[PDB]
Image 1 (cartoon, rainbow over the protein chains, first blue to last red):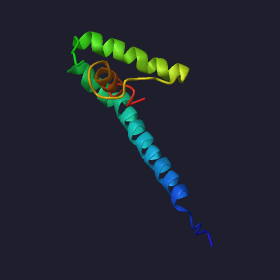
Image 2 (image 1 turned 30 degrees about the vertical axis):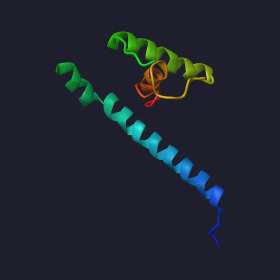
Image 3 (image 1 turned 180 degrees about the horizontal axis):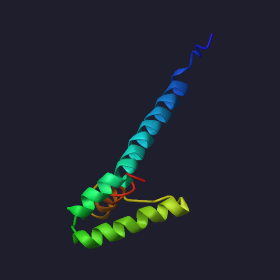
Image 4 (image 1 turned 120 degrees about the vertical axis):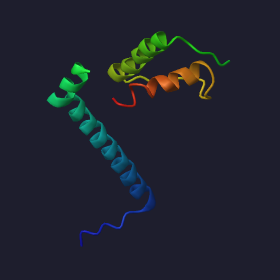
Length: 46
Length: 52
């Protein structure tokens, strides 16, 4: 019932949205790693 | 034609136009093909605009 049979163009926009969300998640955890305390101490010390 | 620049001038000015496009949301007309100034601004948006 919750099985929306999307056409090809709608499905393609769903893919493009999903790739965008993957890129935001990856850049966000890279941001969290580069702004965490431990990495700041490491880069500062070196 | 294809050229090359100093790394400090390429990084600072390359960061300047890409964060200009962040605030103003502008359209950026280029030559399109990767040679010279277009190859420099492609690497410029791939420098810090690819992470923002």
